[PDB]
Amino acid sequence: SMSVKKPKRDDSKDLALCSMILTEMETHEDAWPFLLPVNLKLVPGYKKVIKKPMDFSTIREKLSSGQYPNLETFALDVRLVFDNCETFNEDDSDIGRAGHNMRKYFEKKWTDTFK
């Protein structure tokens, strides 16, 4: 509270470490459904159903331009990628299985890096 602060967690490497994680996700062979934004002109239903589209290129741009205030907002956008994928795709589809694999991959890198 006022003039009573918790100890300082060192966050000075967070930017670099999230960049590294994102590189690893971008280079995973199952990243293909997530590399670019879904083309809302060509994919029926996507625009109306998925209220907050997200993709890795958009996260990369946001990260590169200071649009994440902290590592939790970065993680929120990554998870939104996989949440959207589960919303729109059957579990037993190539894209649906890709999304589950990438979420697992991410959460392991996240734990190993920060927790």
Image (cartoon, helix red, strand yellow):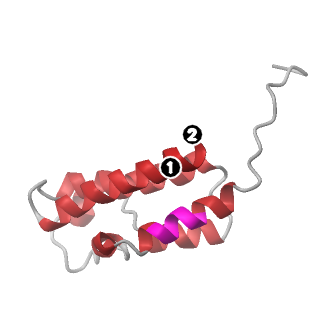
Q: Is residue 90 left or right of residue 40?
A: left
Q: Does the magenta segment cover residue 61?
A: no
**Residue at figure coordinates x 27%, y 74% from the top left:** 40
CA neighbours of label 2 inside 10 A, class few (<14), some (14 to 19), many (20+): few
Amino acid type, mark 2: Lys
Helix, strand or loop for the magenta stretch, by majority = helix
Which badge, 2 or 1, is on the more N-terminal residue? Answer: 1
For the image, the number of numbered tags is: 2
Q: Is residue 93 visible?
A: yes
- Residue at image mark 2: 115
- Give the CA separation, mark 2 to mark 1: 7 Å
**Residue at figure coordinates x 61%, y 50% from the top left:** 71
Q: Which residues are magenta?
A: 19-24
Choose top left, top right, bottom left or bottom right for residue 99. bottom left
The foreground one among 5 and 104 is 104
**Residue at figure coordinates x 52%, y 47% from the top left:** 112
C-beta proximity under 8 Å, tags 2 and 1? yes
- Above or below residue 4? Residue 44 is below
Q: Residue farthest to the left?
A: 92
Q: Position of residue 30 (x, y in %)?
A: 28, 70
Q: Secondary structure at mark 2?
A: loop
Q: Is residue 89 left or right of residue 21?
A: left
Q: Residue farthest to the front?
A: 112
Q: Position of residue 64 (x, y in %)?
A: 64, 71
- Residue at image mark 1: 110
**Residue at figure coordinates x 31%, y 74% from the top left:** 29
The foreground one among 55 and 99 is 99
Q: Secondary structure at mark 1?
A: helix
In the rendered view of the protein, which quadrant contains the C terminus?
Answer: top right
Q: Position of residue 92 (x, y in %)?
A: 8, 57
